[PDB]
Image (cartoon, rainbow, N blue to C red):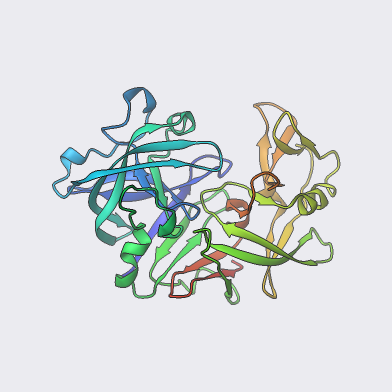
Length: 330
C-alpha cells in the first residue's frame, strides 16, 4: 500500500503545516501537524476541557462505530516550546492520503496548554519519530508509520514541505518526480528516539564551506533551524544590523535586509536554504525588526533541522531495519 497527502502552511510565515487525517467511521477529518520529532497521535476531542477549545475541529469517539476505549491508558506530553497536552486513549481507524491503519492509538486530549488553544488551525499532532518516545502508559503505543510499515510497498515516508506553498507527505514510495539530482542517504541514530543524523558542515551565502560535524534531528514539527551558537553567529554576522535580542528571544535583523542563503552538508552533498526562507517577518505587527529563521540551539541540548531546513529539500525517512535519512535538492 501507499498513501499521499497534501500538507498546507497554517499561515503566511510557514509557522507549521497541517495535513488532513481521517479518523473513525464514518470519517472525521482533522487537520494534524505531522511531527517527526514526537511519537504521539493526539487530537482535540469531545473530552477536551471546553474553555481550552477555540475553533479546532474535534474528534468525537462516541460517533465512531470503530472507536474503542483503550482501558486504563493515559498520555501526557511536553514539547520543546513549553507546550503540553494530556488525556486518555482510544483505538480507531486512521487514514492518511488513502493509507489506512486499523487499531491506531488516537490519544484524546482532556487538557491542552494555551499555545494549542490559541492556534485554531491545528486539531492535533501526528508523531512520526520512533515509537520508543510514545507517552502512553502503562502500555506504550506505536506511531501511525510503525503500524503502517509492514503493509507499505517500501518502509519509508517522505516530507516535501513547501515555501509559502503546499507540499506533500508520501508513505510507502519515493516520488522520483519530486526532486532534482540524486538522494544522498546518511546514517541515523535512534538512541534518543529521533531521526538524529550528522550534517557534514555549512556555508553562509557564497562563502566557503566549513567541514564540521553537526549532530541534530530532522524535525518537521519545529519551525526554525536551531544550530550551534558559533554557526548561527557566523550567519548573522553577514547581515548588517542583525543582533541577538534577549528581550525578543533570539536573533533579529532589519526588515530592510536581503538575507544570505545558508548551505548545510549531507555527506558530500549540499542543501541550499535561500535567504528568503530565513525571514520570519516583523517581531510584532508593524515593527521594522524581523525575526530570524536560524537560531542558536544553546540551552535546548540538541540541534534541530526544523522546517526552515527541511523545506529546502525532499527528505526521505527510511524506516528499514537500519533507519537512514535521505536528502535531495528540489
